[PDB]
Image 1: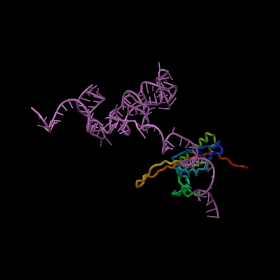
Image 2: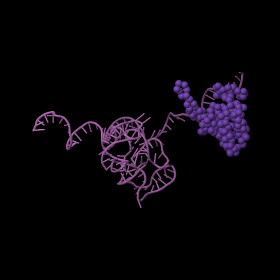
Image 3: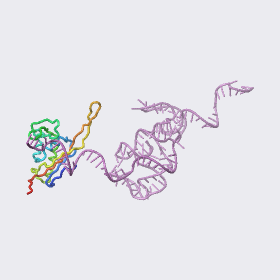
Amino acid sequence: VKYCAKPVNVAKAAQARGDNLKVHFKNTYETADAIRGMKVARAQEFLKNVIIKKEIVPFRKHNGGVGRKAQCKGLNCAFGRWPVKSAQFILKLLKNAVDNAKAKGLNTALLTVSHIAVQEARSSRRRLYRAHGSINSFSSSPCHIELILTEKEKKVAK
RNA sequence: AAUAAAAUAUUACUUUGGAUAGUUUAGUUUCCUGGGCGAUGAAGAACGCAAUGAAUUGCGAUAAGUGAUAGGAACAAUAAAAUGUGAAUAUCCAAAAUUUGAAUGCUUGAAAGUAUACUAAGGUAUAUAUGAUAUUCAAUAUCCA
């Protein structure tokens, strides 16, 4: 599966990717939106606090039936959750993208999560047995996750 | 009044999905030649057989093949062994051809079985109906001593 975007300078970027990951797309789509643009060190700390329910992931688009929380103040979103499984899956991709950067020879402290994208994947079907002799579907919602870490520098064009 | 988180709109890239284009060892129809099955056991069914096979294909206790005749150097997924002193391959031929099935000694459900005769095992034959011939008979049915 190809990447949504290519780095501006491949010499100063690192990539990680996962395909058909067995994690919910709607939860991971909100976790990736939270960590997009922050430094790699901060993004690793934020995802660890989501795990122990100390920073919230604001559910901005998929907020149907989600409850309100005290950590959702100032984010322009009244709803949030702490998706642990999607935080752990992104953490394994963030790590893999850092040893890829270390192998290249980039300063890890200067990296940032420039591009992270979540895509839908083919669902797996199961059986749920309903009343009056019916059978419904019990479908997973896997996803693809891309990740590009690029170094940061000041931009000036005269 | 204000924010653009959600919402909406366009383009590029990616994804879910498999339309479109190109293609065809498959079909459909018409015509030509035959229309060549079986008690010498058919069609159908079952089971079994490959060095590593489950299906399918081929084959039948001589098993993915035997002989003969043509044929001339391969097979392969891997390893063997054989091979111009003849490998693949082909056949209206020869041998061989498990259990059934018209199924036919008797029984048969998913049944394992079993009788007699001929030639301990193994192999043959013994259903019903029927034509011809031979042989043994039955009925005073007609004569008849």
